Length: 290
Length: 159
Length: 177
Image (cartoon, rainbow over all chains, first blue to last red; front, side, top):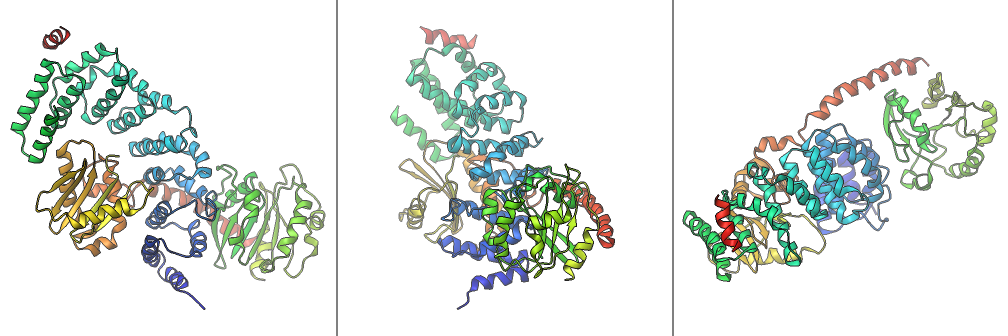
């Protein structure tokens, strides 16, 4: 009549965490199949709200994440609210990495009854001086925006003002990515502002705007000058990425004989400079289109 | 030992707890869930579930239906409200058998906080007067008071 | 995102490990991918193939392939750095190379994907430093000693209580015309 589920249970005792680790791996593999039959849940439940083992928690957590959670128990196993309060604390945790890590997870996470006061909780965490933590919120939020955008409704602006408060490029970059997805307009307003400053700045964020601008004109234009003013500055162009895009965007925008020429040059030099052949071909292909 | 703090926690039922644990107070949202601490004595380390007796959480505790070893009832001694009603619930604990594996303490908390009943008055009222197949000495705390508690407890692990 | 999955590959027709940024489907997207990869399509050499607007990006590193996938345009170099970069990282991450070591440090490795790359963004430099961020921290400790201690005092005390109780323009005009 008895089973090795139990066999694992003693091991855990035996080691502690260590044995449990082993158990996680096994479980994992077991999990990996799909497969498992419940009961260890209880164990897990028992020891884990009163236990640390951070790594293990990380394993555990992730396991929860990858695995379902709207589990035939509910929805939730049904404790998805209670346990969380420790976790919420952790999420609260003064302990910034710890929160950040959670957040990382959290971006992956999407479990609602738990979320609601964690909405409050998160808000606090944004304030924490760590850009890692804050950045993590940007993903997380992104995750909300599709899942329950509304959950938070005032956000697009809130962000946008936030940007104002902000200055970490990494976070900014992110900020843009999400911001346009929420609404371009805010980005644009800012865009107006930024126009001169751009040149000074780091690429990655710059890139993101290039996509956005594209979609809108085919639908409707009349907008140019303000852009142009900048755009000309962009006709410096110099990173291999920048250049790669820069001619590419241009064509998207224009095809005047003068335009034709501008881009063309960029290529030709580029090529000449160019080394990865794979690359070379690619531009051709564009060219082939052209 | 598994020691149980039930009733709706957020009232400072949890305060009662936080006061033990750090010395502090409810600096949490009023807390439905398991709150866990281990307290070590006789080095039985008492694992305390301070759990709100709020709706689900009261409703659902079956995995925690296992076998008890210690009883705190943390009390609003201004509550003198849900207790009869409680008595009415409480029977089903009585009707549990896991529940008869603990020599316990009801703790009257929240005394300063408004008032409290006759130690007796309560005793019938939750239905408490009636036990014996578990010990049943009585101990008042408050939640800004409580001492000699430990006498209560002393007997209790050493039952 | 700029990558819905990173899967690290071994020659076997099979990719040694993988992670699914986003779940929905089943492996058949991933499963199918795995199959195709194993097959290689007999194709001779070349470290890149994109077909059907899907980049299949790989790097043989030995008998191993590290693979990334994408469909719409990218800036190459960056990418390369990564493949290569992977090829810098592993003996550190999971220990050397042989599946097993990795098999033990799976968690570490997956963690590295996330860590390294937040949705197709090159997050940092410095591997050790990368360790640092989590399961290697600092704050928590600082807090713990003081706190734990404080509580402990309360507890200790408790034990007793218990116990007893121009240029632009050129263009612009031309264009303008």
